Length: 194
Length: 195
Ligand SMILES: O=C(NCCN1CCOCC1)c1ccc(-c2nccc3ccccc23)cc1
Ligand SMILES: O=C(NCCN1CCOCC1)c1ccc(-c2nccc3ccccc23)cc1
Ligand SMILES: N[C@@H](CCC(=O)N[C@@H](CS(=O)O)C(=O)NCC(=O)O)C(=O)O
Ligand SMILES: N[C@@H](CCC(=O)N[C@@H](CS(=O)O)C(=O)NCC(=O)O)C(=O)O
Ligand SMILES: [Mg+2]
Image 1 (cartoon, chains in turn green, brown):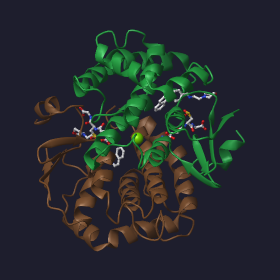
Image 2 (cartoon, chains in turn purple, orange; image 1 turned 60 degrees about the horizontal axis):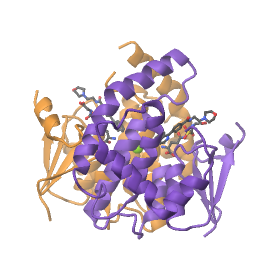
Image 3 (cartoon, helix red, strand yellow; image 1 turned 60 degrees about the vertical axis):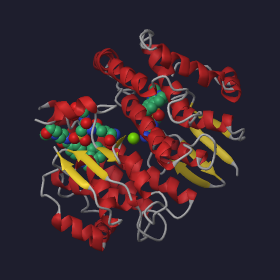
Image 4 (cartoon, protein in one colour; image 1 turned 90 degrees about the vertical axis):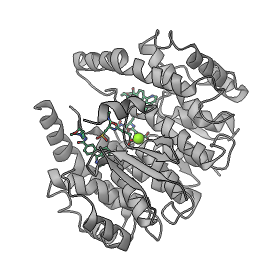
């Protein structure tokens, strides 16, 4: 099928979809914008993915759709549940940040609270969850591992010492970044802050 | 057929979608409604509820759990594409409901008022538009997105009674969900809580 991804010029919520296309070697149009386009969207939000003239929305709904019946999905139905659960736990936390807050003091207080109080607890929980295992779910890479690497990359921009106590979580990031298709995308993609 | 123990507070909240699914599929489960929380919280991999214990193995994330329980059932969506549509509608609803500062007074009251007055009507319009005159939100039969629509809108109605005054078709969909026999049976029997 013809795939057209529409999002801002940034990694953000589209990047999980971009990793998935890269890994599965699926050609797509990576359409990066830039008030007018917002009025055309089903729920006024991006990313959207057009699939042969059908408009899909919700980054994780799309990500899950693209990984159905592929090696990035969980190998069992319970593994798929763990994959979904880890992704929503990550998405929940990232969604707490006031990305679009215009008041700079309010934004700084909230980012700081989340990074200094909430984030370390989540890192601890993820590290204990991973234990000594190779990937987050099962015996091979899933799109949960991709999403960990994507979210932690952005968190590290704001809190460089985030993973100083979690070398196993750093090792996982590096393993995702070492996957040939992912490594190639990381080196060729537009360099944006977020 | 596994042993299911659902752990949550004594309320509909985020556990209710799971309770609807168990009801519709006629699955026996322990509805564990919890002073007890500090101890229980300390045993959970991610410290949040709901969790679902499946033969003693702890699953978390209400929608991950709901999706798991609906796999290979008539609630999932009839194709891979419909399954995407179902997931997208559920996340759009969850996104909005998760904006509310449930655990935050004054600032809490202000944010509720803003969300309900300024944002909710926009979302209702978009949902009505998406429904597009059809009987159900995705495809030709009920999915767990319809269940979630009914659950989320029930709670929004507690705070904003006029939520659907401009959307008769959304009221009709709620009533259709509420009339599904297993759902109707659960609605009449469940503990009565505000939220
Ligand atoms: O900066 C973000 N959004 C504002 C977009 N803008 C475009 C340019 O002009 C106006 C501002 C933003 C959004 C999303 C995320 C993000 N990244 C990775 C993962 C995420 C997961 C959930 C929620 C947000 C996530 C990070 C930053
Ligand atoms: O009030 C809520 N949660 C705090 C419950 N408490 C624990 C300690 O005892 C008293 C207070 C709450 C949480 C969740 C929802 C909720 N309902 C339906 C759907 C929802 C979807 C997303 C997020 C929240 C949702 C509504 C209310
Ligand atoms: N859970 C959904 C949220 C999308 C979203 O809110 N996107 C932002 C843009 S950016 O913060 O990713 C959005 O659409 N904001 C409103 C706007 O910019 O008009 C998803 O993952 O697709
Ligand atoms: N996206 C997740 C959110 C779970 C959550 O934050 N749960 C709250 C309770 S609330 O639903 O009444 C929670 O467990 N908070 C931590 C606490 O209360 O200590 C889900 O849907 O399962
Ligand atoms: Mg979510």
